[PDB]
Image (cartoon, rainbow, N blue to C red; front, side):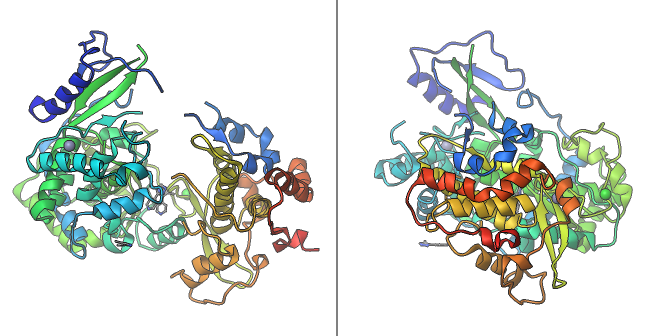
Length: 574
Ligand SMILES: Cc1cn[nH]c1-c1ccncc1
Ligand SMILES: Cc1cn[nH]c1-c1ccncc1
Ligand SMILES: Cc1cn[nH]c1-c1ccncc1
Ligand SMILES: [Cl-]
Ligand SMILES: [Zn+2]
Ligand SMILES: [Zn+2]
């Protein structure tokens, strides 16, 4: 409690001494409350006009148009039983060693951090003293503040590492110290599939289907894809202590700096929350996930890999009960990990809180005691109801997608990502933040269009809309995003060949594709099942009259150099 968090709390009181009070009508039951102080302030989703003018048939589809319009944090998780705590400690110890065999923990640098801010990563900072991250990083006074907190952390204390709720934004300084100590997990790809066997970090949406098809090839039971209800709110203090064991692999300054991030900011937290009754509440708690989103991704992947290996151990009968491991169950658990752990990791695809598991057999479906007792309660099923698995890898949900096997005219086999097309069009019609020029709006539309050409070329409506947007935006204008092989001014046919043929390890024949007409679509009925408007009168008029829509947008942007991409399609090619 207050010996670790007091200084942060003490400091905040004194900046708002004219406003402090122990408000007696505070809604917090599971968060420890400290005080309140006067403030006044809050950005909604804005429509991208370039994408909307080129997707007119979707203007009357509520699932698209509603996407642009518009008491889980205040719960507590019970402490796991002694048997569960032992399983988690043994598995976590083993997993950090496997992940560390071919990697070396190391500090990330001011230089590395500076380069990140200078090409727009979502580091979750705040606006004050400087306007933006770019300005703060370029100012020697910032680094002096960073230095003060840094020496405080080496001394085992904290003053300014406080979360702001809304996503848990910190000041750029606290973000740096997090990245210095734990950035290596992402920067050096600890959760790549090569390094972690279950992980998919850095793999790309064009590989995830092939990875699930490789898991499907293993002998075993159904494929399980159980979602957890509010994963970040079910991270226990036992979880945070197993995660901290990465520091056992560190040395020198780095070990001390990383131990301080875990001890002072993760296992103890201070948060400011807006309450319209508009005060700022200063609350603390020990458990749940509140890191930067990139460290959150890696530690979620780690704890998810651990949880799923334990659920596999439960299905395989490695231990009888979570109440208590006997001396010899401990040796059996250790021995399972050493002899088959790596094989059992290869049976999984894990992206943070999202997993797919192909267990040895279907005993897994009813192996629920460790999973429930670890607090990883499944979403949308009763606590003790057996999991429903998937019999076909092409039906399994993963990372908001499903995956199709698509046969090219020349016999070669693509495995492609897919999701309901209303979700894809709805997302592309939305921009975030203020002060967007027409050029910037056009360049964001072009980013969506090029992603569609690379990932969703097999959807008739998206290949046509992608071609239309690329025809409507000046040819040399560079795709942008405010938070990815489609981010380029290279010819997208050249990029398609590099991604799906040349660099694709599942494609043995490397014969390049000469034109977009060689690149196939889903079956027409499959395209409709996944939300295509092909067959509707609105869609036929849009396709036939597309040059008129392209010319509307070209007239708004003005007299620029444009290319016609529509004749890359059979139906427009004379
Ligand atoms: C330090 C620096 C400067 N220009 N590029 C790098 C760099 C890039 C990628 N990995 C490590 C270093
Ligand atoms: C977490 C997230 C969301 N969209 N994409 C990712 C991602 C990208 C690359 N490697 C791992 C994850
Ligand atoms: C799109 C998404 C969501 N969660 N994770 C991913 C992902 C993972 C790995 N590579 C690319 C993307
Ligand atoms: Cl199925
Ligand atoms: Zn601190
Ligand atoms: Zn589909």
